[PDB]
Image (tube, rainbow, N blue to C red):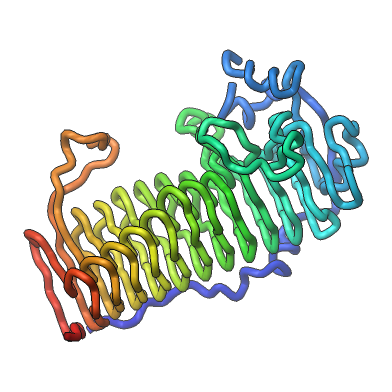
Amino acid sequence: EMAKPVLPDLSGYTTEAALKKIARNKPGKITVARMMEETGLKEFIGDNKMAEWVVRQKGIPQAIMISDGYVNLQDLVKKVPKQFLSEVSPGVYVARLPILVKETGIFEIDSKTKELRLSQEKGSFIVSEGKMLITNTSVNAWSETRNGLAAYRTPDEFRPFVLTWGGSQTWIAKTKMASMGYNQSKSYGVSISQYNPNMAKVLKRGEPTGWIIDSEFADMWYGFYCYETRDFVVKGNTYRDNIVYGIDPHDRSHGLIIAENDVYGTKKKHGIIISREVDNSFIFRNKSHNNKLSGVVLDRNSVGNIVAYNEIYQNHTDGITLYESGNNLLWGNRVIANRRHGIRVRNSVNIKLYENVAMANGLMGVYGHIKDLNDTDRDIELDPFDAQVSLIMVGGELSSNGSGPLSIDSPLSVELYRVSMLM
């Protein structure tokens, strides 16, 4: 029938490749100015909204700013007052103001830094409108009160985060990060974003991009988040014990590479979820296991994607769930012992399920259904749907699931070819 999928070459995505991606030759200006002077800060916060930051800083709200050239952490440390950027032990720093890398800025943290602690109480965080590279180190949300990580307690309690804007480029490699992010726009944890639709009209910057490679993310509100992002690469990472999602690419992102990640322990929702027109992307060779909800989710008209060769096991609901995201290819996933269904397809058409293995799930191996979603929380205007399900199933195996190999309610069409179904 159909040839096996052609998946992107991951071999270029290297800490060594990464290090050669910035221009270090031209420094390097460092100011400490007021936050409200800067578009890159106004765009997720500000004036009638600066009260919280005045409280956190105990004074008129200020940021550390990098622009026109190159600055590393150690560079910042020397020029910025101790009260704001303090080295508490060799290689260990506490930032007590947010750090903004401006458009012409190039900011680097490398192996010279043991750990950079963002102060929770003083409301520290990182925003980059430009070039940023973080390699061989730790950047953690840090409670000065608790003398430790700003461990998660409640959704609305601020924690430090990393966010990047449109026009920017970001490479994180061999880096550890913990306890970042909370329930607040563009503040989810590590967030890659185009500008808010208004400001993008004016700035006309390109969609943001970069890599997150061989890094580890724990206790994040969302492990990864992105909005209108192009060609971002998430390879070789561990997402452990995060609060809401492990990896959460969003809102018209496209051409993404999410590969060879180990995503588990997600406390509230899914391991990996792409949502709202996340198209033409690749989710392959990932371990997504033991999340409170599903292993992998394609949601809200996310189309033209390839979910290939993923190890999806022991999630507390479905292994994979497709929600109103038609025209996707699931090839050769091993979907094993999830508490509910192995692969569930709701309101999606032309799903191709080739060579999947669905074993020992609590319910059906493969389950396809429809559901009228009109008088619900769904913004039918933003996220339309059509209550029809159709799928092509070729090869693979459905075995020892609790409720049976497959069940497809009211399908428009289902074709099955040479599928193994053991009794």
Furthest residue toward top: 48
Residue at left 83%, top 31%?
Answer: 31
Q: Quadrant of residue 392?
A: bottom left
Q: Position of residue 237 (x, y in %)?
A: 58, 64
Q: Quadrant of residue 130?
A: top right
Using the rendered image of the protein, determine whether residue 101 is visible from the camera's viewpoint.
Answer: no
60 w.r.t. 293: above or below: above
Task: Tell me if 270 is positioned left or right of 413 in this view.
Answer: right
Q: Where, quadrant-wise, is the C terminus in this rendering?
A: bottom left
Task: Tell me if 31 is positioned left or right of 397 in this view.
Answer: right
Q: Where, quadrant-wise, is the N terminus in this rendering?
A: bottom left
270 w.r.t. 416: above or below: above
Using the rendered image of the protein, determine whether residue 115 is visible from the camera's viewpoint.
Answer: yes
120 w.r.t. 422: above or below: above
Residue at left 55%, top 59%?
Answer: 239
Q: Position of residue 410 (x, y in %)?
A: 7, 59
Q: Depth check: 206 or 321 in front?
A: 321
Numbered disc total: 0
Residue at left 66%, top 56%?
Answer: 171
Task: Tell me if 339 is positioned left or right of 26 in this view.
Answer: left
Q: Position of residue 324 (x, y in %)?
A: 24, 52
Residue at left 85%, top 57%?
Answer: 112
Task: Tell me if 291 is positioned left or right of 84 in this view.
Answer: left
Q: Position of residue 143 (x, y in %)?
A: 71, 38
